[PDB]
Amino acid sequence: TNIEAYRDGLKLKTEEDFFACDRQYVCQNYAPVPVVISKGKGARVWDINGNEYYDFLAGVSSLSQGHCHPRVIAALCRQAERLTLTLRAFGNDVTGPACRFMAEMFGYDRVLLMNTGAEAGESALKIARKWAYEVKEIPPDSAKVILCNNNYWGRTITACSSSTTFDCYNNFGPFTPGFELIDYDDVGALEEALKDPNVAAFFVEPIQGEGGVNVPKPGYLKRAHELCRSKNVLLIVDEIQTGLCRTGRLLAADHDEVHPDILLLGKSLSAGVVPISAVMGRADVMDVLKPGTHGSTFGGNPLACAVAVEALTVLKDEKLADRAERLGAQFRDCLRRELYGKVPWIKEIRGRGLLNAVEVDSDAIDPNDVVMKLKENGILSKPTRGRVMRFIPPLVITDEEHRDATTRIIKSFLAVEEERK
Amino acid sequence: RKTNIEAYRDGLKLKTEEDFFACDRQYVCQNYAPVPVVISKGKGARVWDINGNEYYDFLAGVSSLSQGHCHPRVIAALCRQAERLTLTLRAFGNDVTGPACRFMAEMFGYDRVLLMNTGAEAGESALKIARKWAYEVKEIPPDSAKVILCNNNYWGRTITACSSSTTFDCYNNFGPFTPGFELIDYDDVGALEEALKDPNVAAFFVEPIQGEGGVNVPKPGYLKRAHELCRSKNVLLIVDEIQTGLCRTGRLLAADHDEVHPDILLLGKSLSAGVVPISAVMGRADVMDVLKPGTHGSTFGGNPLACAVAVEALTVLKDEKLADRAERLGAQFRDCLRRELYGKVPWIKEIRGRGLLNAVEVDSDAIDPNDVVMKLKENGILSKPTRGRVMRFIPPLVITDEEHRDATTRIIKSFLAVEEER
């Protein structure tokens, strides 16, 4: 194909040839791990030299079904030969059914399909504001949305305006007003913020992903929802990274028996094949988006809908939530037993399901040394906040692969501690 | 062997178009007022409904389907790459993203390529780049950056895009808004010159032809004059070619009509031939390099599947000489509609466009716009107006000579029939 023919013509043999190409032509907004991946299958990837690795990032939980899941790729191909895009300006024979499928799977009246996670977040903020002005009847332009320090939901200007991460907002203002930032995992702070009747919504992650896999105290989300409901404030739960079986339940909110007023999904919703995200909620909230008040060229395109239905079905068929629960408990147990005490620079081992992290002390060790040693041992991952090592493999990882990977991971921390001496 | 969507849909027993309309009303967020047609397949310039009725698609994803529905080369490239690798994230290298960026950098003449997913993301990204550049290179005061745009502009649905829109339904009840935008009339060099006196302006963000605003073609020299004014004040010219680029107007970029090379170029829509959402922001090194590691990202932006598709989609544009095709057919389209409709149909305000980005604006007082839309559908033409009264004719560029002659006759027939029935 054209990409293959063009690449051949470039005579890119070595990993360095590729690194140089990326440095010259690609916007330099990433500091990638130095590997050149050419193929993915399941929990494994291979570089251009045939070296194999376990992918322990999985698209930050976009690849829960593994790389190139056969069923998802067959669903993609089948629909792609037929029809890929109509616009929501015209009806089609896939969008409605796919929305019904999601509505029933998650228990919501209405499904808004967008492309990216950031778009789902923006759309939920628009819904929450418009609902607050039209249904709660709060004063024009006074709507407030409460979010948490260290939250991450995207890179639009409005997301930058609601971030507390320096690099995410610095020099990108002026900023969108209307946000109240409170500490994460702090019910007392939320209770206080909720005293303001201009609050439209509280927007939160069940586990802060980019913030460093921050697992809140028992009852947090349950308590939060009761406080919000008490004040007629919408609970917007972002499950883009925590949802779809990654934490051992269909939704991470299920850990607290919470049904979000507005749910956000994305990432694994497409098994990492094409960008698709969703915003779901009750009729009286979602219906505020009247014709012409919101839209998207590719949102709900038939190709993405066909992929999403397949991707969601794979989660249920392969019992990936039970897999994540079982393997994750094992991973944490092994790491805590074999690394705590032996490795003094490990601050904490935490997570739920297969959303796990190892926070290291960056004053006691170079975290990049851990990253490189892991790769040397066949494990590929990328930390968040420099010091929080992340272990987010595809959920389809086999028992043997997971055992092999756990062993490699443990060996890597140990080799960095021995090298410290 | 049925895939899940197929089996699930079969279980719903949806036989008529009305069964589908009802499913959509119940479960799909009702933010669209769709045309009553249920499309099941598309090939080239044609689509077919669930009952096998053929239609010409004259919206083409608002120029997302320039290469036609399901272009076989593009679908083949998708299927090939999808069996190999679809997503790595930019946290890891791969054997596709760099090459695809180089391919684009060379085709459009830019140092660096930022790949995102949607058009709105491209525009957001560009605004962030312009702001950051203004703060760091122009050294304007903190939080004082301004961006000039035009009334009736359309670039997205994010809160920041709403904050810079003059369309009521786009911004109403979605505030409070992102500050930092100065709105001026489109196609008004004097208004731009005045707005450029503010030294805190970082950029002027403009479409070479306003798309959602009504296929508003500016006067001769507009974009060229704009660029000179922007250069004079060290203000970046951000040109949005998401709808106008990629051969739609008869040239690779609509900016080529004025020999303007945008400081920052935005592409999207037909960049993927309508197969998967991919968009691009391109610019010179000292502008794009303000996005340092960790200051911007995207999960799917630059994914290998989208990159393979894009390179095939762009190659189709060149190989099939679609810019020439657009130029030739589009000139014939406006010529035929003017010769057969001006005078004979009095409620037509103007027939305008460039290449195959054409519109027929009607006087919504003298006629009900929707009667034209329905008559067009009766005659096998699917279209969607903008601003109610602006009829749009945006077919895939791959439409054959025979298909285009046929379609033009059907459109003219539809306008005259609404007139006879008037």
Image (cartoon, coloured by chain):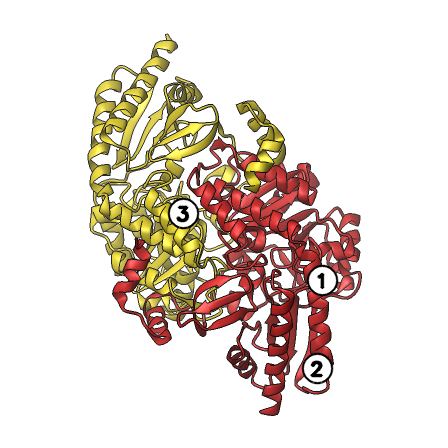
Chain colours: A yellow, B red
Q: Mark 3 lies on which chain?
A: A
Element assignment for label 2: helix
Residue B409, given in percent of the width and then of the height, sits at 63, 77
Question: Do tags 3 and 1 sit on the same chain?
Answer: no
The CA distance from mark 3 to mark 1 is 53 Å
Q: Say left or right for A195 vs B294.
A: left
Subunit under mark 2: B
User: On residue A38, which mark appears?
Assistant: none
Between B301 and B404, which is closer to the camera in this rendering?
B404
Label 2 sits on residue: B340
Mark 3 crowd level (few <14, some 14–19, many ≥20, 10 Å Cα): some
Q: Distance between the residues labelled 3 and 2?
A: 62 Å
Q: Which residue is drawn at 58% across and 58% down?
A: B155
Give the number of the disc on residue A181: 3
Mark in the foreground, 3 or 2: 2
Residue A311 coordinates in the image, percent (x, y): 32, 48
Residue at mark 1 shares a chain with residue at mark 2? yes
- Disc number at residue B327? 1
